[PDB]
Image (cartoon, rainbow over all chains, first blue to last red; front, side, top):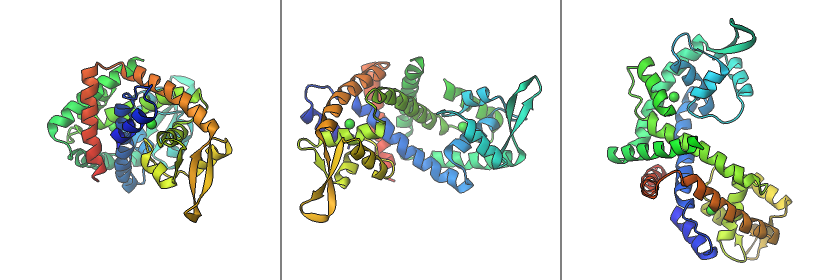
Length: 160
Length: 161
Ligand SMILES: [Cl-]
Ligand SMILES: [Cl-]
């Protein structure tokens, strides 16, 4: 379907080289479809993708699962915009607590609660199984090549 | 990279788990977020969101006189995700599209690009292509070709679901 779009541009604006639209269109379509598959599993734990990401990132820090907002933001799988209202929501649900920084009275830290820890330890197991199932449509060799080519793209994008 | 660091954290914290699937998917999603930022920065110069750009571009791609049924429009957007209702209304209010009665079914309408919509998208698509070319220039042509092929395989697999 992406090639069909490229063919439309070749007909309608032949003065332009629309070739860059192909890889990016495929990347973004894959990402939307992938997000749907991931959310289908997060929903079983009454979590959104951004909630899972925050809890998983606190889990990955290791006990006692305390991160500064900057550390949290920097080690999320995906960032996009302020955390203010999202952190407030996760505290309202009781999965994190904002705690005073003992080394700076004017700032705070984010800590995973016992209920957040219990939940994310179960959710990450299901998430990995879900991801393994999603990717099972690709041969191992294709997945490996895709991973290395994405890492090359990611390095280029981050270098900008 | 940052995804390798995340995998290292999981290997330390949950060694009972094989976090291998997280790698490619994490890289895919991070690339998409960064790509969206680059695309949106360019669209913003034309006071367009990515979704608005897609609707105008899809009507442009249909060829003159740039009339599509809502279903044709949706089926030829570069990226679909959710209803078109609110975005179509905004584009109509801004005067970039007009809803016209379907002469073969009075109870339904067609979406037509207006001349102001056409003038805008003819300029914006030129900038969009140059923007995308610059974004992808971080890859050698051979690596970009391999990535495009790999993504096509993943896309076909995801669509089969
Ligand atoms: Cl993660
Ligand atoms: Cl397009």
